[PDB]
Amino acid sequence: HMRIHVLCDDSSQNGFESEHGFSVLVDSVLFDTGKSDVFLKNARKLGIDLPKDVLISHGHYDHAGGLLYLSGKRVWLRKEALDQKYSGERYAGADWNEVLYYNTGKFVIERITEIGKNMFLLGPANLRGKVPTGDFFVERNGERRKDLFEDEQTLVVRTKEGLVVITGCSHRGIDNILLDIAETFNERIKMVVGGFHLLKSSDDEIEKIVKAFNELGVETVVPCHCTGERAVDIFKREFLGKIMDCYAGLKLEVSD
Ligand SMILES: [Zn+2]
């Protein structure tokens, strides 16, 4: 069997700490690392040793921040995760100078990158005419542009039961993300876990997304982090499959 552990999230079960950020241990690879050391403290609570490989979904502080608490990891990030991210006038980037001092960067350039057996990183999703919601900017060279999240990447784990998809915030659209996966893998999408960033999306926008989950035959959804209570309620009432509650304690077990 293959195990998954939420090590950081906005919610938590008794005993586990929580912050605004996301981190989930997926078998032999760590997906994101929260804002601070909450992921580590939760991991110690479970008596887990973290693996060599840490994957970064995008270069926001709440996803890349706990890297400040690791050394010697192999950090899989997109080159464009290095650009300094703003959210409004608020700096929201990560300290890559420090992170890459203590750790080792593995830069992801391809659309599809194989990590280990049956594990893949998929690059920035095709926006299909949509553009990220929110007030996000990015600065390359002191040049302030709008942020399209060219740094965003998504983990796909190929299971005998179908695909397991792990996403950090889905700025490019969780629907775009799934469709990109759908065009690449002949396999069915079994489970999707992570943040979908639906707090600033309209109920219509969210229903269209749930519709895509249904259309693609997704069986189980575990919405974390950015997703939002409203959006989850819509998932619970319109998604044809099972929705699970996400929290820092959470452990999921799934077939190889
Ligand atoms: Zn983000």
Image: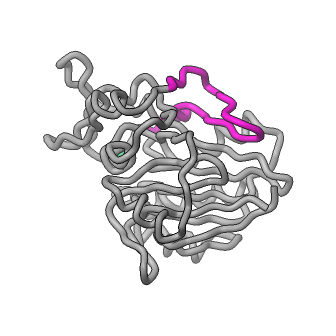
Residue 158 in sight from this viewpoint: yes
Q: Residue furthest left?
A: 89
| Colour setup of the view | one colour
Q: Is residue 4 left or right of residue 72?
A: right
User: Which residue is situated farthest in the top direction here?
Assistant: 141
Residue at 40% across, 25% down = 80
* Of residues 50 and 199, the one drawn nearer to the viewer in this rendering: 50
The boundaries of the magenta stretch are 106-130
Residue 208 appears in the figure: no
* Residue depicted at 25% across the width and 34% down the height: 137
Q: Is residue 239 left or right of residue 74?
A: right
Residue 193 drawn at (x, y percent)? 58, 58
Q: Is residue 103 above or below residue 51?
A: above
User: How many labels sit on residues?
Assistant: 0
Q: Position of residue 201 (x, y in %)?
A: 39, 56
232 above or below 166? below
Q: Quadrant of the N terminus?
A: bottom right
Q: Residue at x 48, y 49 (%)?
A: 168
Residue that protrudes farthest toward the bottom in the picture = 14
In this view, the residue farthest toward the right is: 160
**Residue 171, image quadrant:** top left
Q: Residue at x 54, y 25 (%)?
A: 108
The image position of residue 135, as x and y in percent, is 25, 43
Assess whether residue 233 is covered by the magenta stretch: no
- Residue 20: name its quadrant: bottom left
The verdict on residue 108 being magenta is yes
Instruction: Assign the C terminus to one quadrant of the image.
Output: bottom right
Q: Position of residue 252 (x, y in %)?
A: 65, 68
